[PDB]
Image (cartoon, rainbow over all chains, first blue to last red; front, top):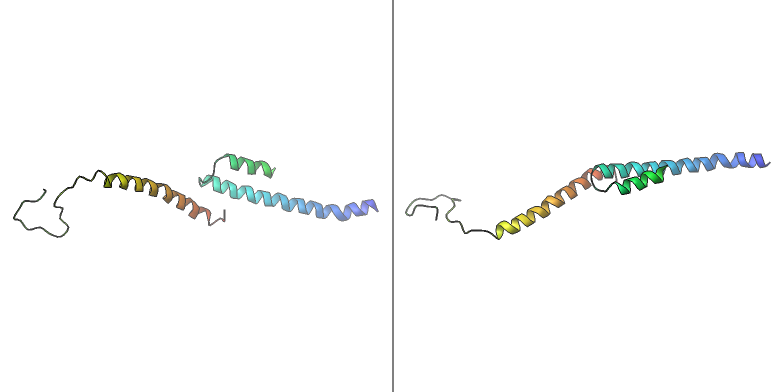
Length: 53
Length: 52
């Protein structure tokens, strides 16, 4: 019964984690575009790159 | 006084030179302000397509 509960929960918990990862990746991509246009410095690119992984 | 007297002048011909020296100065200052905010607007124009 504990195994069935873990099976019923982990597939949704990992989906939530994957959505979090892809949201952070879109954040990093927009920050990289904003860096290479020249608006921001390298520090607030590196912090978003850090938050990504 | 850059015209011969008693002549015929046309529209827009320069007559004198009143030694600007202040108008040139604040023209330079406004030119510097425009030369900043033009790039400030152009980068935002490039960014707003990607919704950054």
